[PDB]
Length: 50
Length: 50
Length: 50
Image (cartoon, rainbow over all chains, first blue to last red; front, side, top):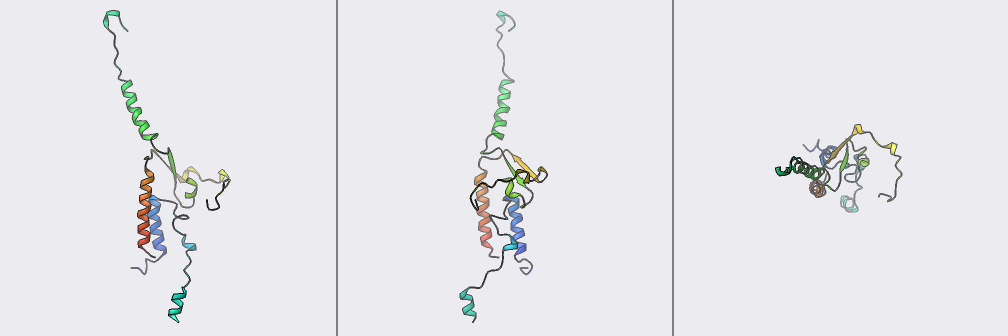
């Protein structure tokens, strides 16, 4: 079921959770999805690929 | 204080009752580190409640 | 704290009561429980790499 349950879903979920107990997650706790831009590949990843 | 021979002592229900309920109101509302904490419905304004 | 320095928040900029839930009669130790909630949330969020 992971294929559906990716990133956004997870963040929403977790948030909700938080939002029940610790509210303002947005900006001190968990980076907002709009800005959670994917990581650049490492030199170790790249050199092993080539 | 009805008459000199009557030994007009007076009971203190009312007083032992008030201090009772007062004991508990203070224990409940003035006990905490704080009086109140606001809470928001949205992460949009969570940063203001504080 | 982000720049660490009084932001003169035009108060009128604030939200309305409409949006605001208030609570009273806080436990003197709400701190500790909030903290344990946070560390539990932390173990959790660490558990999932996504």
